[PDB]
Image 1 (spheres, rainbow, N blue to C red):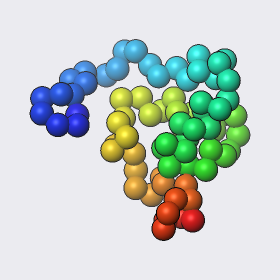
Image 2 (cartoon, helix red, strand yellow; image 1 turned 60 degrees about the vertical axis):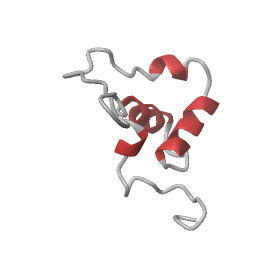
Image 3 (cartoon, rainbow, N blue to C red; image 1 turned 90 degrees about the vertical axis):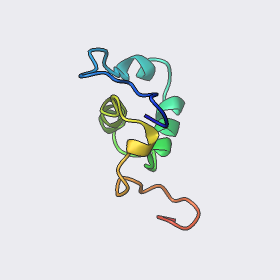
Image 4 (tube, one colour; image 1 turned 180 degrees about the vertical axis):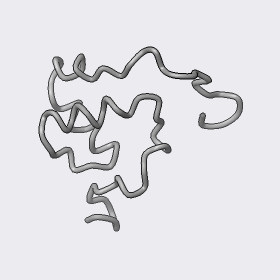
Length: 77
């Protein structure tokens, strides 16, 4: 987890991160969330959903360093 004994402590997240639900809400949330992953919020509708869906159980610090392609400050920009 972040620090301490704070963690998900779950072996296989039975509850999925079904982003299809979010996708019904709008698309702005989806774009921003991709940017928060470190992407340029691009790709196909399918791509956007898949990446967010697959972040199942992964925290922000568990996002791959090479996955960050978002133009920010002095990296990828």
